[PDB]
Length: 95
Image 1: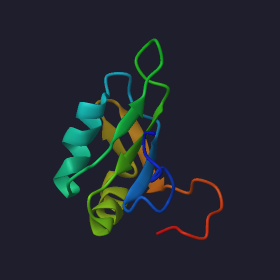
Image 2: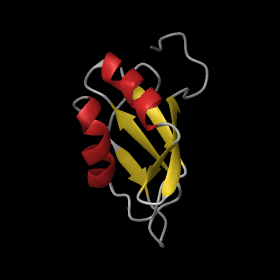
Image 3: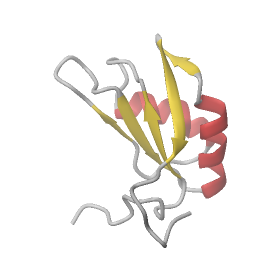
Image 4: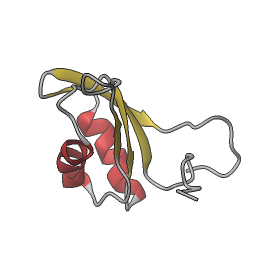
């Protein structure tokens, strides 16, 4: 498999919207890691650079909450990103 923690129960799971094409997993990690360790961050990239959204898996639950407050509404390289709680769908097991 890949990772069954791709829900809201992966601890510290957040989603980011409106990223710049120059944003890679490294770039996302480089910024958000300051809030806490990341196990699996991802910038879903289009041919031109990025589809305009990314995801963080934080080591710690609290670090994720920091990333949400701290990064939401900020400019990353040029584009203001929206960071929020990763609501995968509708699960009972979710934090």
